Amino acid sequence: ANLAAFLVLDRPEERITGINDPRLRNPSDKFIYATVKQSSVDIYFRRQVE
Amino acid sequence: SDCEPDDNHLSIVTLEEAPFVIVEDIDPLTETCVRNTVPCRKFVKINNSTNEGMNVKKCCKGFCIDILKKLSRTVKFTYDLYLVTNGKHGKKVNNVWNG
Image (cartoon, rainbow over the protein chains, first blue to last red):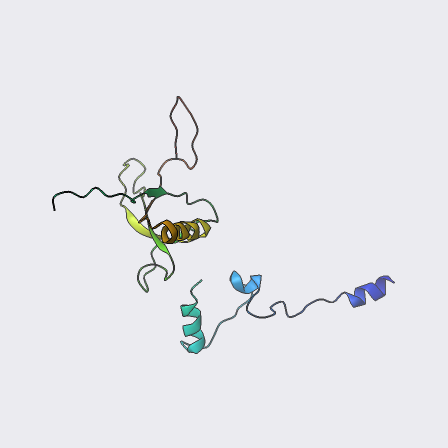
């Protein structure tokens, strides 16, 4: 039963699930993520300045 | 020119020690502040002996800032922010408060 429960418990649903995530809200040094350059994504990020 | 009795100044002092109001300073880029923020002036401590402090403008944003903005857009009062120098909340020592 313990082995079955441990096998069932896997979680790890990519830990992001879209833009709305605490990891993306507060930047983390360990988790590195960014865009390429001053592209439309960069303009959108600057426009939604929060 | 001659005289004008007006009101709605309402100087406000806020504490830079709670998550409801950030301590963000002037950034070198854009308009020296955030696109969604309000000005706030705080006396600085240039030296440990001299109490003189330059009133450098700062960008204050937070829950209290949003509440103040809503109040301003509702009751139409033109506000100006401020920050105290000694203490945050204070206490009644010899009938004198602080903060």
